[PDB]
Image (cartoon, coloured by chain):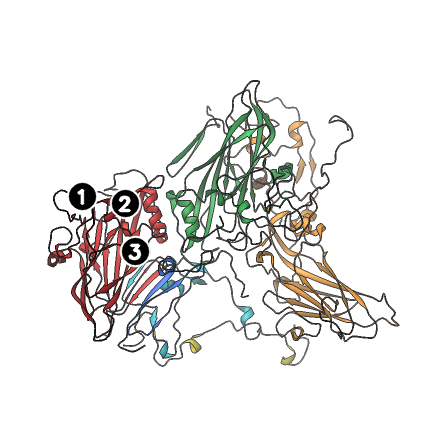
Chain colours: A cyan, B orange, C yellow, D brown, E green, F red, G blue
Amino acid sequence: TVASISSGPKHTQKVPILTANETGATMPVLPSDSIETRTTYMHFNGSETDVECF
Amino acid sequence: TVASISSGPKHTQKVPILTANETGATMPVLPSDSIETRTTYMHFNGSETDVECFLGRAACVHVTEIQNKDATGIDNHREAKLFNDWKINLSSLVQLRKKLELFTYVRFDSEYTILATASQPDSANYSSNLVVQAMYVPPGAPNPKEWDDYTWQSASNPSVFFKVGDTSRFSVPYVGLASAYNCFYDGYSHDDAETQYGITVLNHMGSMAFRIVNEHDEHKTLVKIRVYHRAKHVEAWIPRAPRALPYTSIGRTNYPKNTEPVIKKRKGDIKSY
Amino acid sequence: INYYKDAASTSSAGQSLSMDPSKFTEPVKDLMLKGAPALN
Amino acid sequence: INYYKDAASTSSAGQSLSMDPSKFTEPVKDLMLKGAPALN
Amino acid sequence: CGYSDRVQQITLGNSTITTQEAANAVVCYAEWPEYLPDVDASDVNKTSKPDTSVCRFYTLDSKTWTTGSKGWCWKLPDALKDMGVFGQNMFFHSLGRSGYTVHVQCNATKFHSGCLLVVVIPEHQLASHEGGNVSVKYTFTHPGERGIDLSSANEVGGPVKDVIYNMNGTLLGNLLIFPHQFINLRTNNTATIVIPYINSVPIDSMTRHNNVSLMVIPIAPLTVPTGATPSLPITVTIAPMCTEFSGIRSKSIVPQ
Amino acid sequence: CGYSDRVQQITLGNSTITTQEAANAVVCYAEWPEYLPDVDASDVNKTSKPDTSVCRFYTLDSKTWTTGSKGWCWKLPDALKDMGVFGQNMFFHSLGRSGYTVHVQCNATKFHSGCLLVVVIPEHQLASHEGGNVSVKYTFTHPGERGIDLSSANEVGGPVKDVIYNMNGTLLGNLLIFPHQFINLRTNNTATIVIPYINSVPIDSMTRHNNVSLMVIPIAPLTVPTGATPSLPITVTIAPMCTEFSGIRSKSIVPQ
Amino acid sequence: GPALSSAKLILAYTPPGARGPQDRREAMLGTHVVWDIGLQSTIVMTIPWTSGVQFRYTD
């Protein structure tokens, strides 16, 4: 599973970093949406954070 | 598998015994290259020399004494030996430290085995049935401050309880932040003129706190707790030059001033046997 | 292998592997896609 | 037979049977065969 | 089948090194230096690869090998912190990763005698001369291009200078386990060692940590012919190779 | 068909610029910046392309637009000579080539009135105020990030500061032939101009020559509401784009 | 602030190893988002994972 996707320069009329937190929704904005990133993997499943483990 | 091949007389312009060690290569010259040999077999696999076998047997890493006595009239329960703390590191015992410090990076699963033994140097009529608590305090968790502190409740911290005289044993996965433990670090905590060199949170496994959970009695019993560590699933990288001189501190490469010679001087000249 | 009759005797179920934070992060009536204006 | 859930609970893996000392004994750019002149 | 092996040349960027008395170059652990792959990466910032602007040979100030010189020690990448664009990028980026092609040169006549052990030690963690639990100060472990002279006297808060104990408690005869080459004046004028990135992490701080330490130690002492100067010049040439930089930020502040 | 055009965002390297009152960005001569092709190249040294390490937005010190301010002038690449790795590479290489994404910002309330002409002039060769055959000294033509204030007094060996005559003998109303955008406070808070490499040669000296000159000139004077401060802040943001460097050499020496 | 009010702000993240920034020119040298306050009332700047080591301590 990919953690960060490969992403280059951005020149667009769609701006993912601007929103209205007044709606009560926390937008799923990623590191790739504010700056240019490389492809990396999660290489982690999150078993120690399960409600059964906590 | 053949150890030595069958080999007869040699008359050739190719000379395998002459080389240039200046190249940094150690040529794989065999007994069959210098004299005439017979065919023999290895009849050995080398299982006892595997890195998993060389590092995979138990060795003591810490020894500590704790006491069951009343906490009245004491300001420090750790200085009264009512509970004791161990900064987790495998560098306190030189027999284990030299084996492990022979590599630059090592990644392994741990297996701790704790042996608690009782002693009554003062007057006691019976062998008390004491229960010891070993509590793992990872970095950030509150280290116990008193033998009856709220921290010992251990709502999330791993904790083990066992009878004195017997033993406890629990496995621990690889806990390092990096992909392998750093046995050596040529660097600092931050870019500072007075900061610590080598010893840094790269070698910070956490702490272990030890107490007698049983209440205090009329007689004083000294309990020596001995921690043994045995490595499993061992991987090692970058083999290193072996340690020669005695050590002086945990996590640092220092040696004593005025140290004795390590080369065993010969009796007679360079020609004696 | 289970050594007892009751389900309460069993060990943990491990982890619930299918997760979805959207029901807590974006519990909104109309669906909002990132990059499009939140309001218009 | 493994009696626990974690890989850290397991016994040793035995031995890594495929060995190759060449990466430590001869870490040289050009490959050198014994009997031929090391330098020419 | 007519050819020679002593003649080899390395061209990196706009610099070219030529040789006529070389021993086969060494590649540490038989692994050529390479860029960080996606399957090992941790930081998500896309890495800056400056190619020919930093991947070229830099000559460090020559040292003078006398009959009483004990040896010399350099730390990387610290030794290249004032070298062109590599030195600036190394301070302008928070994290960096790089391999190196080290080339040591010591030329002499057919009458001179002596042998140098050129060896690269990963995490060559130094010991202080004061013993006990004393730490080596940042300023003595990060000297830059002038390196550490093992012939000099010990200093307060500094590392120990006994070359035989490798400044860390191991004997000199055992350094041959690390990637090494000998400059035997009778056979060679140059040692060459290609180093890949050696660390337990994929990319790391270049200002707080030295990945490798280069040591040049005379084993057989310099023996000059009757009437020649009892000194010989040693020049060390290092080129960053397969270099990666990540996390650009304001210029980094270090002691001194 | 429901959408808006005033919201646009530009991400270069690790920097992101966002806007809510933008006019459509301008691309000089409808040509997006690009790397030098082999069919036009002259110098044979292979070019260093630093990508995300230099291709990002740098903010220049804000200027204060008052009711009596005449205008402002910046020279490129001179204005970026102290900006991170771009500033160092620009002095460590003998030749360089680069495009730029200029973004000028001046925000105000719905009661403010005024209009700025943001224009890019290739080879904006300045005139001295002394007339005759007097030359403009290097130190006045290469000010760096603080730029040239056209509201200030004239200086010995300096350029002329009459904004109406564009500091070169042309009238201000004719500057609209060059790639330009207006920041009309009633309509916009930001001007944006993407510039390709403009020169008669494929690559050139970055220390001796300024390829373009950015001018921000208030046409309609700043009119603040009754009781507001008679001043407004202007911030200029510039990002090198499609940058090429060639001919690495010791660090370049310039006046002052 | 009011609907007729306006402001342009620069959010700047400085990776470790470098001093805490003393000026906008120093902060703008690092990871940054220029935010124009307008119809969209909220900005969302994601701090990219910048580390050599795979895990950092919470303490």
Q: Nearer the viewer, residue B17 or F92?
A: F92
Confirm whether residue B162 shows in the render: yes
| Same chain? Circles 1 and 3 | yes
Callout 2 amino acid: Met
Residue sitting at x 60%, y 74%: C12
Q: Of marks 3 and 2, which one's residue comes earlier in the chain?
A: 2
Callout 1 amino acid: Ser
- Quadrant (top left/top right/bottom left/bottom right) for the C terminus of chain F: top left
> Which disc number belongs to residue F135?
1
Specify the quadrant of the image occupied by residue D25.
top right
- Measure the C-alpha gap from mark 1 to mark 3: 31 Å
- Residue E165: x and y in percent read 64, 40
Q: Of marks 1 and 3, which one's residue comes earlier in the chain?
A: 1
- Residue G43: x and y in percent read 35, 70
Q: Which residue is mark 3?
A: F239
Q: Of marks 1 and 2, which one's residue comes earlier in the chain?
A: 1
- Residue F240: x and y in percent read 29, 53
Please report, as a chain letter, where disc 1 is located.
F
User: Closer to the camera: disc 1 or disc 3?
Assistant: 1
Confirm whether residue D1 shows in the render: no
B67 left or right of G26? Answer: right
Q: Secondary structure at mark 2?
A: loop
